[PDB]
Image 1 (cartoon, rainbow, N blue to C red):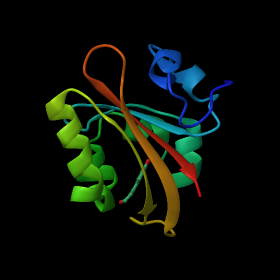
Image 2 (image 1 turned 180 degrees about the horizontal axis):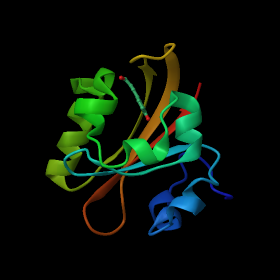
Image 3 (image 1 turned 135 degrees about the vertical axis):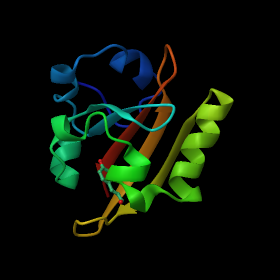
Length: 124
Ligand SMILES: *C(=O)/C=C/c1ccc(O)cc1
């Protein structure tokens, strides 16, 4: 898929893309509901983190999968965005739960329709 990390209209491009198409992206992509449950999780993300995508779909990202993100610096930003109904933030972070610590750039953006939220990830 021909989409760049951080693209201004990424929510339109990805809107309603199915799991197979998401697996074509150059960067990790996770779709979360407003509670942080995982709705979609692509192959590039699994390559970065070791998680098996179909296994983490339905789990809570903050509670279960990624406790290192349960902090004001990641989850706090996410929940503020869910509560506001608007989110577009980009920041670096280190992923380190049961994995070699890995520095990444994270872009969280509210999905176009409904109430879903993207978490995009690339190595830095
Ligand atoms: C910290 O616990 C981060 C873990 C993590 C981040 C992103 C993922 O897709 C999976 C686990």
